[PDB]
Length: 229
Length: 232
Image 1 (tube, rainbow over the protein chains, first blue to last red):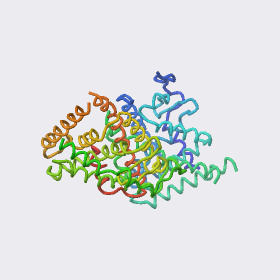
Image 2: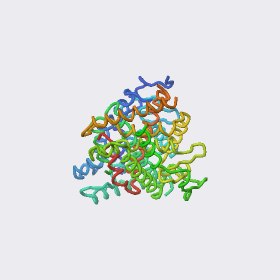
Image 3: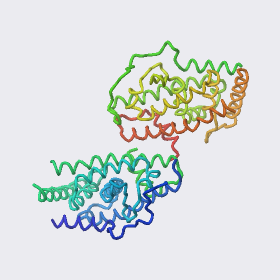
Image 4: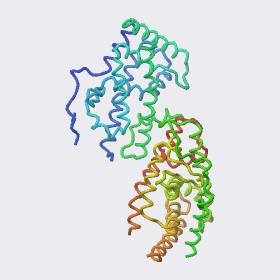
């Protein structure tokens, strides 16, 4: 309710307004992988880093978790968060990727840096779009990606309480707007999203191997620490 | 030559002969669920990597000069080149025109039986097999090339110059044989190198992915190679 309103205010402020979109570099007709492409891949990921952290700071309860638990939840869900907010923001029917700064790029502008990762993300975006998720449901869904069980939490029961809180909040709101199914269908995108995060881990691994441009330290850290091994 | 003979003898004993070919598990049609794998497929994949590594170790022990290198340099050369050796010997042995993969022990498996454990990687290895076959590399030229893949400069050798001397030795022997039989085939064969190098990368990606999945843990020595051959 007031929780819901707070999750919404938090989501909308964490992205760009249709007025602040930048089509400056957009090329629908785009005429191996080189170092401009690898740099732009890391830059686009790096752009959401501070955005998602300020967004999490505004989820009620998140700052009452232990600071070690806050950092680990962010670090463990960064990739999934980046993917869900990009899939929701973008327009997959026209190949349009919209990033959280407002930059708009065509997918062919992105294919070389992202690999086929990017097509997988556009299929998920089509899929998510067909569900017609409203803004309050999405503001709940994304927060549930963050605030979830991870190995090594100091206070896993308090993470679980807050998750139940956000879940109840999502569950009402859905029921209120059209009396499993809907809910079940929306929660089904959590596991797709985990599998899609896998695919991003594979892409960083591959690029680290190539080593045209090294990943920036904080991307490299998230990659190394979220690898179970 | 005498080196030649020994390299040749070492190669033929390391593989199977058109007899000892096991069709015990061969199925000319299986219907898999693509892009997924259970723990039987993953243990078979590793088992095939590790059987091939004990076979390549015994083959290297027979290359004259290899066993008196330092034990550490011996291991590092093997591990540094295992994946490349594995793909080359597998490509050379196999029959891409019937979709057949032939391993080490004699085991024959259809491309469709490999799909789950190996991923896409196996199809790309079959494509390189067709590639390598159209070059028509004879057994004594392949016995030389194979060994020059192992005996090579690697960072961190205790005695890189002993390795280089032996590399010179096998190169000369190859050259003698290319002339006895008479750039490419050479330059033509180095032209496929990038295919191979991509396939080694493609195998690292597959182990990474399966280590992520963790249906079963990789064997320790495969895991060690994966890790120490990753600069990070």
